Length: 155
Image 1 (cartoon, rainbow, N blue to C red):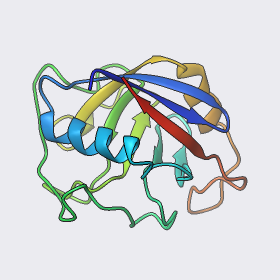
Image 2 (cartoon, rainbow, N blue to C red):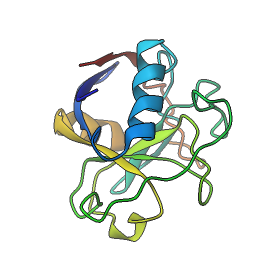
Image 3 (cartoon, rainbow, N blue to C red):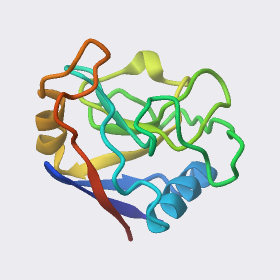
């Protein structure tokens, strides 16, 4: 899988995938995407000037599972980092706790290097990500109006 398009209710985010390096992470993402696993997932956690986060079908914030059921390992690479905004990374709760949840950064996040697997980068629709992060959220950072993934196309 070389690239993806995430169709959302606010528009489309095109992503290149780091398939050479992050083989398992890209597989988890692409298989879920194709099976429709991410369809109707909301952006459940949005933090302005930081990141927008999605990939939990429950919408709770703790939900979602990898294609293996069990959580899987991080895949870190020096050349894959958060020095630029609009990187696509796995959410986690510590080392080797990858499920289905992922985020897109809106600012450089180098403090996340070697803590989150970077598995893609936005190539079109960064303005959509910037639109998403500006929405009104509650005290738990959940948008007041749901922003939804409709489909993810894998190329």
